[PDB]
Image (tube, helix red, strand yellow):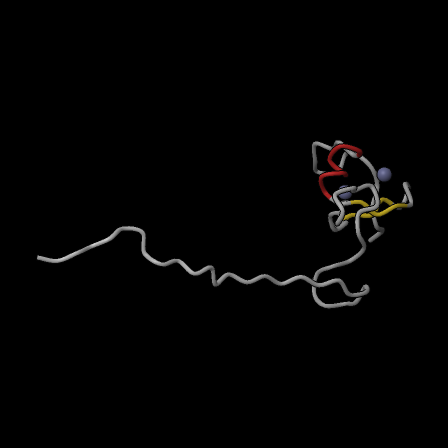
Length: 78
Ligand SMILES: [Zn+2]
Ligand SMILES: [Zn+2]
């Protein structure tokens, strides 16, 4: 002899964290991919000196379609 109801409490105790500071050295940021247009864009982990512009991976994949190891364009000198 007892009662039992379904659908217990569920208080949304979730939180977030947003920020928008200037360009500062923290760990892994670097310049933003100019070709990107995500807004925010994707970090540019590449830089083609010949193109004179810094790009990311994805972009580099479309713009610089290389099948490795590096038979495509050029990058930051050694
Ligand atoms: Zn990009
Ligand atoms: Zn290039």
